Structures are given as C-alpha cells and as structure tokens.
Image (tube, rainbow over all chains, first blue to last red; front, side, top):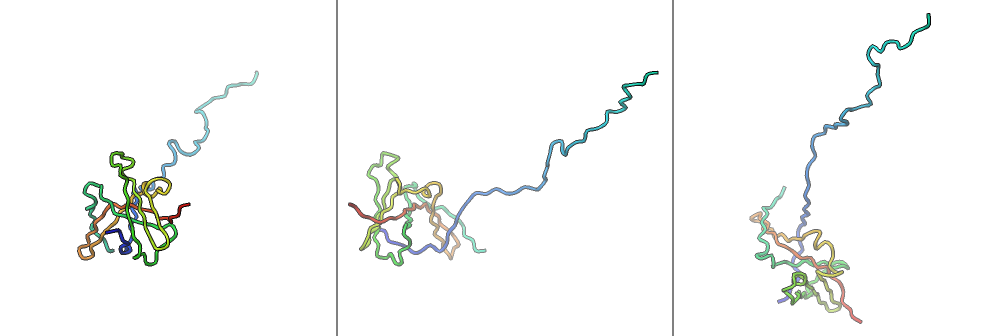
Length: 51
Length: 110
C-alpha cells in the first residue's frame, strides 16, 4: 500500500512564454544628423570706410 | 513532427497531487527495493501548514527524506511548476497532472 518507483519518464517538456520580433525600421532620430550652421539671408555689410 | 493533444484532467479540487522524487546524490540503479512513505501535516486549519509534506524513503542501509517546507524545500518547487504528462500513444492524447517534486536526502541522528 506504499508508494513505489514507476517507469522512467520517456520525455521532458519545458514551457516558457515568449513574444516575437517586429520589422526593422531603425528610426534613428526625431530631427536627425548634425544639422549644419548656415548663412542668414542677405545679411548686408554693417560697416563702411571713411570718405 | 510527432505532437500530442494536451488535456489537463489534473486534480479535482487541486488537493490531489502526484509525487516526483529527486535524489541529491544521484540515481538509484534499481530502487524497486525502496519503500516510500508520504507524511502530511495534521494541521488542516493553518493554510501555511496544510501543504507541508514529508517524503521518506527507506532502504536497507540508509533513509532518505525530502520535505516541501524549510531549508530542504528548494526554489524550483515554486518559481517553476512541475507536471506529469501521461501520453496515450494510440490516441495521441496527453493527460497532464499537477506534480510535487521532493528532493531526497540521507537520514542520521546523534
């Protein structure tokens, strides 16, 4: 009436919960790159010679 | 690839559990000579104690004891859950039951 060893298991199942990968879009930056410093339009000379 | 239809007949009240044993010092080549006795805590009113169980295995030379509580209770019994699947090869149906894992260890007292 006691507990005895039974037949060895024939296989093992290991369960884990996993989600999946999306598409590669690689959206690097809101406003991207190093935007260049640049000329103010027209500007004009702010200096003249004497005479 | 070979697959089986999964069914959790499981435990009617969840009170029912199977019993898995693991020996800390390896395998028993032919344990057919081992007698296992499962002990349960008499206190059924304390939810903490009502699930405490001791599994004892007796051989001619040594005794093994496993418990599901205290230091001997190990992390795998909770972080993970163990089940036993009984596969009917003919029907392809796998019946799945809750299992309790006991880590067995040798008995000596001063």
